[PDB]
Amino acid sequence: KTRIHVVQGDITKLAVDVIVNAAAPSLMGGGGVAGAIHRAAGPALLDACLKVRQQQGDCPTGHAVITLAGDLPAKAVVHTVGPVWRGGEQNEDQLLQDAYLNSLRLVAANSYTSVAFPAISTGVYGYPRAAAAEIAVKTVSEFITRHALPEQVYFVCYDEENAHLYERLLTQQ
Ligand SMILES: Nc1ncnc2c1ncn2[C@@H]1O[C@H](COP(=O)(O)OP(=O)(O)OC[C@H]2O[C@@H](O)[C@H](O)[C@@H]2O)[C@@H](O)[C@H]1O
């Protein structure tokens, strides 16, 4: 689209309004993007995530929260919790959808115009890469069709295989 883009590389480098984190309910850092993001952002991010936890407890699956972004070139970080993949009969598809939706909603609610997304749930949470990307693209596309904000959406893909996957699902629209 004019509004949705596929970029390949490291999400932490993206100068966008908001960067999206594939988080765990704890919100306390992790391995995949979560680690990359935290490391890049610096200690302020963690302090902020603590404050949130302190205030709302664990972030439930399919939901999302927004914080400052510290040393990141972004203005804010949205932490969202993807589902753990359990074979597809445990409402996973819906919950992944919700993750994308609630994220977008928060970006908008906070008057942000641009947002970057990683491939939520496809790493350690073990979501089949292809089914996931389908939901991501469908959900985001349908949403931006209904809404002025966010104006710009970036799908950040960590490898070429995934990048191509997205790139063509997008043309399937
Ligand atoms: N710097 C990066 N930029 C963009 N994408 C990345 C990066 N590093 C990894 N990825 C990709 O981000 C996607 C997200 O998968 P994960 O980061 O493993 O997160 P997720 O599957 O949603 O499960 C999250 C779980 O792992 C921890 O990282 C996190 O705290 C939580 O416990 C995967 O495609 C992974 O390749």
Image (cartoon, rainbow, N blue to C red):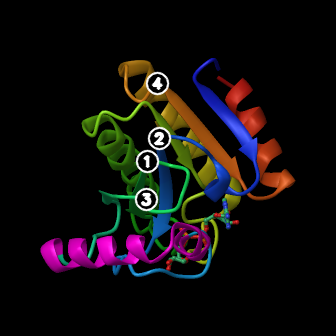
Q: CA distance from mark 4 to mark 2?
A: 11 Å
Q: CA distance from mark 2 to mark 3?
A: 10 Å
Q: Is residue 151 above or below residue 44?
A: above
| Labels 3 and 4: the sequence-earlier one | 3
Dominant SS in magenta: helix
Judged from the image, the quadrant occupied by ligand 1 is bottom right
Coordinates of residue 92 in the picture (x, y in percent): 44, 63
In this view, the mark in front (3 or 4)? 3
Which residue is identified by label 3?
69
Residue labelled 1 has its Cβ within 8 Å of some atom of ligand 1: no
Q: Is residue 28 left or right of residue 131?
A: left
**Amino acid type of the residue tagged 4 in the rendering:** Glu
Q: CA distance from mark 3 to mark 4?
A: 20 Å
Which residue is identified by label 4?
151
Q: Residue furthest right?
A: 160
Which residue is identified by label 2?
17
Which element carries disc 4, helix, strand or loop? loop
CA neighbours of label 1 inside 10 A, class few (<14), some (14 to 19), many (20+) = some
Can you tell which mark lies on residue 75?
1
| Labels 1 and 2: the sequence-earlier one | 2
**Amino acid type of the residue tagged 2 in the rendering:** Asp
Q: CA distance from mark 1 to mark 2?
A: 5 Å
Give the magenta-colored segment's residue range.
Answer: 34-56
| Labels 1 and 3: the sequence-earlier one | 3
Coordinates of residue 108 in the picture (x, y in percent): 32, 35
**Amino acid type of the residue tagged 1 in the rendering:** Lys
